[PDB]
Figure 1: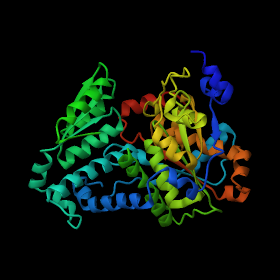
Figure 2: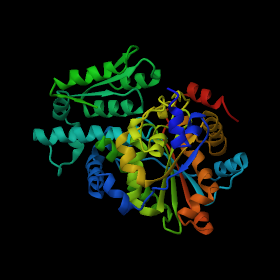
Figure 3: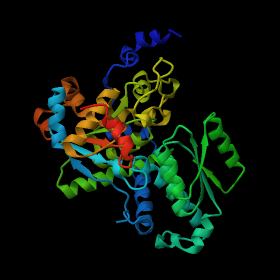
Figure 4: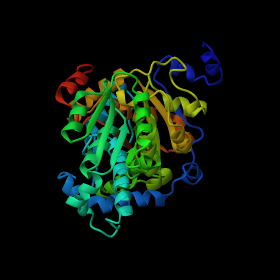
Length: 433
């Protein structure tokens, strides 16, 4: 009911959220890694294992995916021309050097969801192989291409309930390993994603009606098959691998991260999984010199909402009357992961929102300034550098000096749009100049 005004009376910011008004929140409860670590319940070793699993799979991935040293990775690129365009358009200096992480151009799905999805399928494939007696961790994993492996994996099934890039990632990886795969999808999903899945031997089942009881009925249907696996800490750990990989990319480049060369990362957020896991890996890798922020659409501030109020999964955005409708489809998630909120709160410097116009304008501007063409969701991070540079409160609370700031790296994490078909790109570009 109108008891939304009670929440506002206790948490004033909740009122800007309702007004769909662009908001920035700096977390007073951000902490050092040492102080923050306990609440995640994953170590550096859990993360080191994930890398080692992926290394072991490298000779496999390289042969199975010609593009993919067998690593599914993305470029990080400097974007100085985009950087001046933002200063000219919005009038706030961006100190330091703005960069773009192009997870939008990752193999298989052209999405951050590749990281988590692929790691999840690969962990499960490896597990079944090990237990069957077909493989040890000392083997060259190119063996999983053999006729006997293919026949072995085809006796097992993977079922997933996603309509997004995650389903695309798991579908293709699962098919390539050689599982029977069924992605359960809503009729709402874009035609090219169902086509790519099917072009790769995946079974796509669509639901006009009650995508939710279809999905959860599939889960129960799959529970009475012991050979069906139905799709998280594994996903989380999959994203978390991005941390050391980006550190390995800066060392190559000669890019320093220090108390005097701080790094800021701006991460688009839907339910929390992707950006949570990426934040965690970054924290292990760089420590208290990486300052992480989540970005959400004004029409979908689920995590900001949950972290600001301290409620987490207690509250949806629909509860306070926000309609959860946005051009950033893959961030249009009305309730945040409780897990990530609690696990990651202390490790997030703040969270902010932007609206659909800001995403479209910046999308057009990026293309015009750097030739890089992305989707709206992927622009979420782009607004962050100026939120940070503008706030002297935040700067002073974290002890940032003007010269630390001038040696800053601002890293915008692009999350999708590499595999957007031409006619959809024209749609995005036709809303901002």
